[PDB]
Length: 100
Length: 49
Length: 51
Length: 57
View 1 (tube, rainbow over the protein chains, first blue to last red):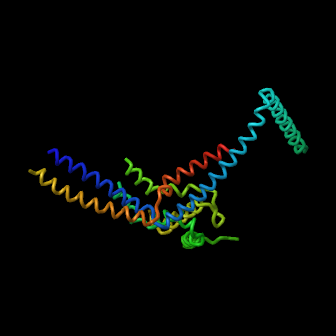
View 2: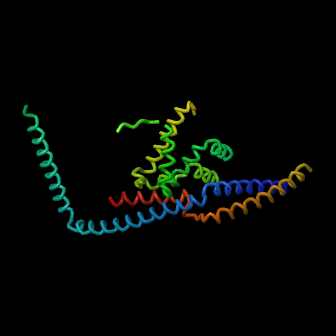
View 3: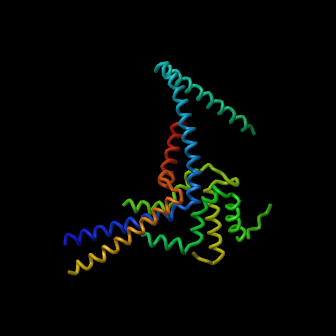
């Protein structure tokens, strides 16, 4: 009984493995493999370019962050004021077009 | 599950070609235009300029 | 479970959506697939062939 | 006694499977298929590029 159960377990495992390998042979034909290679090369070139840009930008931001919280408050205020001026100008332009 | 999906690819030739479309896209643009154009011409549409 | 995952990859072919901005013949792959799907659907409508 | 007979059939089938698995491994190698060229590996690589553009913006 012990021998029989062992033989049954081994046969089921080998069937499963055979069927897996047959599916992989159907999926990756030489033509497709070539395409997958082209796609890789484009993706790899993109990953490399973006990793370099991220590294340069992170280096510049680190120089401003060194001028303290007070500067950041000033920058926030400046930015708020520029945004309000831009909104008011935008409102004046829209009232002139309506003089029928 | 494998027997059902293999059968599905052997019966439907149009689905097989669909699955090959990305291959044509990266290897042969002319073929891609041709394969998609042949399928569009067969469909009569009178384009006005 | 691993074999089931492999069967799934074979059926979906996910590698076709990995480069969206690539244009060939002035159109993206998606656009081409869409064109294909519209054409296949038009052919199926003409050819009474109710799928 | 029935199980002993069935065990003989199972051993023969196991030998048949081992033979088909070798033949399939040989066909994949001739097609130049490497691990990084798989759907799963390439998707994984595209997902990494999107993540990096988001970090750069």
